[PDB]
Image 1 (cartoon, rainbow, N blue to C red):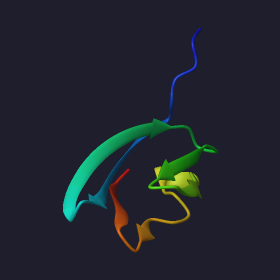
Image 2: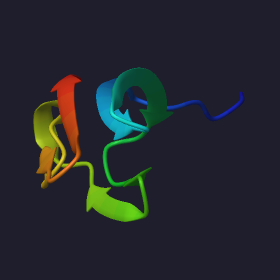
Image 3: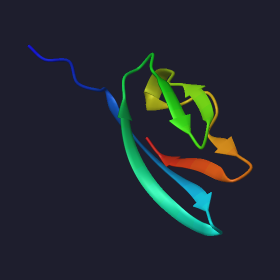
Length: 60
């Protein structure tokens, strides 16, 4: 079988003063990249870091 992600991380980042949402996909154990920042995807699809100066994960 193929290997797909576990969860879809719905996050928004401030680009050019516009909050752009993007849903990315990663596994429990992946490292999510947002704006150059990286966060490990822990349990409950919940990333270690959910908040950044100009970026935030809103849904997982």
